[PDB]
Length: 193
Image 1 (cartoon, rainbow, N blue to C red):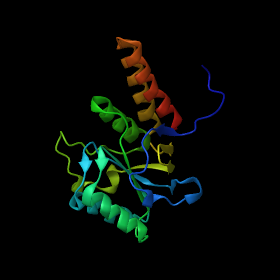
Image 2: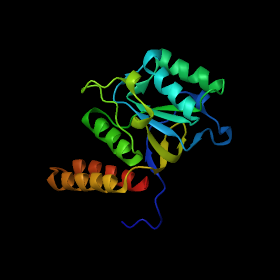
Image 3: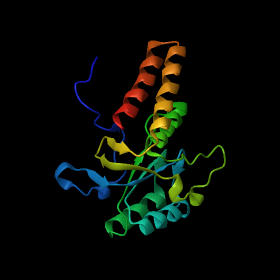
Image 4: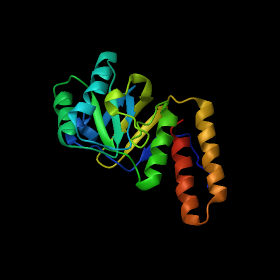
């Protein structure tokens, strides 16, 4: 099953949470150059937990892609109004998958991009997130159905280590279904380098 080409980015089947993020109307897509990337494993709905990071990226002068369980209510509303006013170049999408796998893929993305997942179970506060926790990529492209992360800035050794972790998980898998879902994570990681 050789792939006769180089990587084409890490792509997952989640699209923009608002059409007002679209900055490339020709292709109905959001294209962000050198974006910061926020990874959170919970639903973001309060403006309170969104402003700190927003002011941070606004200060650095960089676009931001937010990947969380979901982004809605006042939080989403604040992202939309500020993006339309041109104060920040943001886009929000739901994290891929569900359950434990959703969490594992959020970590795949964090590792690929040099970011840190803002994890609810361990007590991490979104309002306490800093630029250091944000991941980065050369570019991201989001349309109605997908999100593509191009050239994540993660440490090469860390990314290779994550692939090795998944490889071991595959050997320990008990079904072709599980093995293919694990292999899917490997292919996505390989696509983002």
